[PDB]
């Protein structure tokens, strides 16, 4: 399992309950798990599984988000657990 302190190139598709938007739609996004830049529950959900794994977790959207909308938005994240160190 790829835990913190690693870079997770996760292709996470922001699916809003059946529908798929472009905002939360990220592909091979070289994310850093352990930078505290992503919301709580997101970066982690990817660090708990291995790589090349399809993490279609229905995560919520906290106020911390830069967008007012994703302050309280229960979204469906299709995170393709790809990870680069």
Image (cartoon, rainbow, N blue to C red):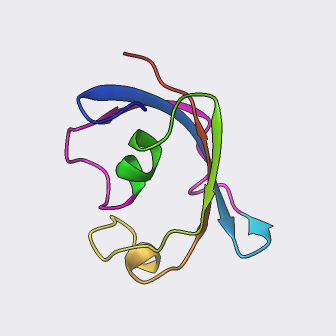
Number of labels in the image equals 0
Q: Is residue 34 left or right of residue 26?
A: left
Which residue is at the front of the view, 30 or 56?
A: 56
In this rendering, is residue 16 above or below 55? below
Q: Main secondary structure of the magenta part?
A: loop
Q: Is residue 61 left or right of residue 58?
A: left
Which residue is at the front of the view, 71 or 84?
A: 84
Q: Is residue 76 left or right of residue 6?
A: right
In the image, residue 22 lies at what x, y percent?
66, 55
**Residue at (42% x, 44% y) in the render:** 48
The outermost residue toward the bottom is: 72
Q: Is residue 22 left or right of residue 63?
A: right
Q: Which quadrant would the N terminus be assigned to in this image? A: top left
Magenta-tinted stretch: 21-41
Task: Tell me which corner region of the image, top left, top right, bottom left or bottom right, holds residue 35.
Answer: top left
The outermost residue toward the top is: 85
Task: Tell me which corner region of the image, top left, top right, bottom left or bottom right, holds residue 11.
Answer: top right
Whether residue 28 appears in magenta in the rendering, the answer is yes
In the image, residue 27 lies at what x, y percent?
62, 36
Q: Which quadrant would the C terminus be assigned to in this image? A: top left
In the image, residue 59 lies at what x, y percent?
50, 68
Whether residue 66 appears in magenta in the rendering, the answer is no
The outermost residue toward the front is: 1
**Residue at (37% x, 47% y) in the render:** 43
In this rendering, is residue 61 above or below 13? below
**Residue at (22% x, 38% y) in the render:** 34
Which residue is at the front of the view, 60 or 23?
A: 60
**Residue at (56% x, 56% y) in the render:** 24
In the image, residue 82 lies at what x, y percent?
56, 28
């Amino acid at each position: 399992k790829l835990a913190n302190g690693d870079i997770a190139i996760i292709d996470f598709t922001g699916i809003v309950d059946n529908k798929k938007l472009a905002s939360a739609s990220a592909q091979n996004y070289e994310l850093t798990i352990g930078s505290n830049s992503f919301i709580k529950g997101f970066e982690t959900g990817l660090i708990a599984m291995k790589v090349n794994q399809k993490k279609t977790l229905a995560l919520t959207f906290p106020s911390d988000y830069h967008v007012k909308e994703l302050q309280s938005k229960p979204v469906t994240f299709e995170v393709v657990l790809k990870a680069i160190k």
